[PDB]
Length: 262
Length: 297
Ligand SMILES: C[C@@]1(O)CCC[C@H]1n1c(=O)c(C(F)F)cc2cnc(NC3CCN(S(C)(=O)=O)CC3)nc21
Image (cartoon, rainbow over all chains, first blue to last red; front, side):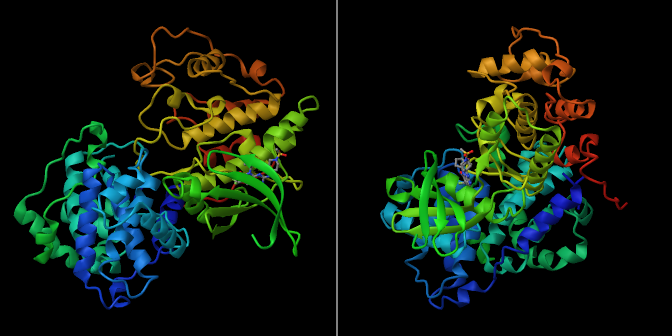
């Protein structure tokens, strides 16, 4: 445990949550009509709706995880079902995570008529019943939050720079767009992205993993990290009605589709 | 429900009704929480989704068990284990007699084990009140109604303000703090510990300012010494009356020195210094119920 309830007890419960929430990197093999890029365009679009409604990064990553894990239970999904499966994964996520989530009609409206409120209601129950109501994962962005606090040392009060968080989050947003990310545990992916913006010493100190635990994910993440570096990282945005100390937790969107091609 | 016969309505809220139900061929009595979906404009309520998922990962002998979830036509039934009574009915029935000190200590010990389990899994209950603490005829007490519960991050972020029932609400919530976590549940448990001892709610306010003044009259008006940052909190007023801290021999007369010590640490103003559920379990007040475990390193 990298943390300073018991330190090892809280940390082991967290590590044993990735071990109970199972996800497979080649889930799109069960859906032969689908190609890995369909998943990328969908997740990218979900990030943009998240930014439009000033939704938290956590609710995007809950929706990403519900979608990828839901698809592992299904078979023969068509390109036309994707928008409903995704917007319904986001409906569940926003209701679980936001204080005042957008209303059902706002979720139907953002699909431009392709999904009705009743279709989303039917889909959220299919999703929740297929996931056996296991809707509380430790997301990729949740690990980044844990690591950013330990870097700037009380672990429950948020004390860390917002702009650095955004730059690491931006790299994770690109990597999640590729289905091969699912081969690596969520904690490993966040620690590897953090490593690309720092070092193994900072990584091990804030995450507890050794460099051999992370080495494989680091090499896989290499191309995604260089495309971000080539373009120059983003600046922390301001959002009306969102407090300054919470601005780093709002999901943002950019040309990640172009960046993913390289 | 083709095998559970509804026997009696035992509860009612914004999202559905709770029934006592008996299995016809087994004789297994359960609590059925019915949520009518056809009446909701937002589908399955956020409270029902949080309660189900959080409870699927919280199996503990001091947490009420969610046995099953059933979707039927335009309804959602949550099946829970049944307990014959809540702590409010028990304290009321024992108001003239009193609750024996060993049973108070045992219920507190168990509630703290259920709470330390929640907190170690990063779950805040946020609705600890006597009616949500269920007892059986075998000396057990369990945490129930996770409808207002929430998973928290490390570090935490700004959560829902209006969160605990008034009489059990912690002063950092009443004073408008931006952040809160596990210490709010410990404050409610401290209020219930004193309520078990005296059979009277410790802080029975009728409004938010009245709740704060009842707290201040008992524990004394907090200042920068006992609570660094109080005077810079959104709802702090320099005009607040200055009361002196009362002696716990008058606040909780039947309580012994160890009981008083534990209670004062659970009702510490500063959420950062308020005792955790894990550390409360190691307090000398419980020495005759638990044995310390050897610690590695
Ligand atoms: C938590 C609640 O008390 C709030 C109102 C409904 C209750 N309730 C639940 O909500 C849940 C689950 F849905 F959360 C499970 C549950 C289980 N068993 C009992 N048993 C009852 C205890 C109270 N008594 S009493 C008045 O003291 O005689 C009668 C028998 N109640 C339960």
